[PDB]
Image 1: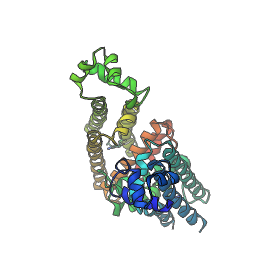
Image 2: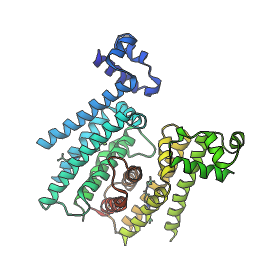
Image 3: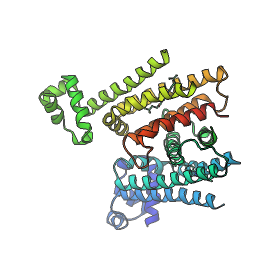
Image 4: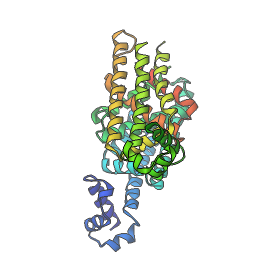
Length: 186
Length: 186
Ligand SMILES: CC(C)Cc1cn(-c2ccc(C(=O)NCCC(F)(F)F)cc2)nn1
Ligand SMILES: CC(C)Cc1cn(-c2ccc(C(=O)NCCC(F)(F)F)cc2)nn1
């Protein structure tokens, strides 16, 4: 019944914002009563937090899998984790980003994983400098932070079809170019 | 009295969110009554729209002034328009960005100027390619879009002291590096 509530919420978020979905809509989709819903989750906001947590953790585990197994392709496969994972869950990505403004739990989840992904990026940049493949230009952690924030804003604008945005079919190549030139460029 | 309402709103936004400022707070700061306020603006939301419009137009006119008068310094002076203009109006930047979620007028203002600034960036990249100084890599407009979105997310995270963020004293150098390497890099 937890999995049913989560699947119903992801389905309804494709059609409309969390504000326009009632606990009643989630209960009915999951084939349970309203008070039975409140047994699994305190709010529709908690449901969105759990959906975002699952997608964020899916991306994180995919990146850890890559890390355990040419330089342009190495960066492209890594950026592709985020493109495919968040791009396969557009409605949860869109709602989860909007909830950063109103939920400290969502803002803290997003902050915690962004810090992890920036640290991972900086560690790889440092390793590339240590092996003599990348030049010692900007502080690695500062470069990593701006490239991660670029991907966050650019991927999510593309997925939402914002004006302006890079078209979704061009966004992976666009980001890979800017990561490789900025990491290897003198 | 319009200028007084605008100055009062900018002062109070430094201390708290628009949600926690009343029309009554704005009237009292401007030395007018509540109904006199409603003569100049329909809402506290309209006041924020006007403040954002003034800051956005200040940045735009500064960039047009530059455009009318080495390549790394050329990009740095241009990015610096946004760093100094928005960085001199942090409270209006912060509130105006948050209002994109809830005001179609604010989202449309932001979209309209971002399209203009991306078009300007692409035109300069095109001119640099035409003169043989930059290589023909990504589509200029796509590269411009991602670099503009990077600056939007990275500058505003720095100004807000978000975790994560590039420190404000390092953000101009960070962005200039990624613009120059991505525009001139093979
Ligand atoms: C496979 C490795 C050898 C290379 C590798 C790629 N990395 C990486 C880290 C973060 C992001 C990113 O896109 N971060 C924002 C995530 C957001 F916000 F878009 F969801 C993209 C790529 N890190 N290491
Ligand atoms: C002086 C010229 C010869 C060079 C020049 C610089 N340009 C430029 C355009 C946009 C932005 C930017 O930062 N855009 C996001 C604005 C935001 F969102 F940060 F406020 C930064 C620099 N364009 N041309």
